[PDB]
Length: 286
Image 1 (cartoon, rainbow, N blue to C red):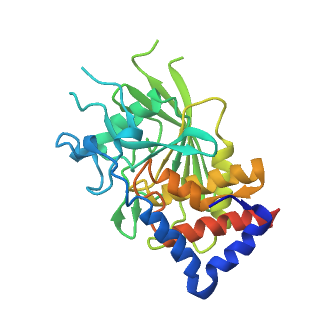
Image 2 (cartoon, rainbow, N blue to C red):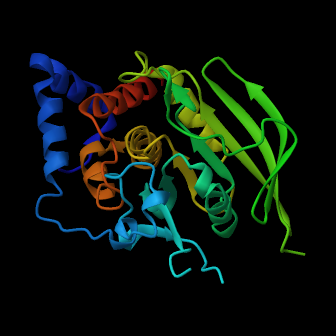
């Protein structure tokens, strides 16, 4: 399970695709099994006091990597369904989290302030195929207040496949009290499966990743559950970094690693293949 030289990676992808994607299936089954001999606790996710804070009953936040909110003058006011996840050669490069619920909007933005997050990556529409995937946690226009955080929409650019919203947020309890937060929102996403072409997503990953500023908190990445598309983004971004640093790729090894940090990151075999397509586009595009 060593790294694959980048110059051999597209050849590797041909082999994985062959025979009705046998190789991809083997890789992904190995991913799903790599948890087998591991008990990873999620006690806080399962506490009765926190259950209404989880969008999905089966999508939990592992204790050891969970993001903790500073306590409030409830013993469980520290909980949010979110985990630190490593990036390439960097611990806790991301926070992967669910699309926030109306009831967790205050927690959501409090986390963003406390963690010094400056980039939000949103990889879902609020509604897909007539189904609620995420609640709108930002102001349609001007300002909105979420607890002690006031969020102000400054500018929006709407590209073909994604939208960039520039916010300024303020903490009303701080007297240094304002920060820029940029949201990268991928908008062109099929209700079922993954986008037919990887290039639009590659472009989105490159630009949202390049927006990361030295030196700030982890980039917040969410979709609906915050595992499938979220894991897909994290692997693509991280492997682009590895390619740039060492001209090698290790999709399988890196994914088995982050799977210990949030459950189900990269949730389907189709997303696993899509990661490869995106990296293929990057390699061939050069």
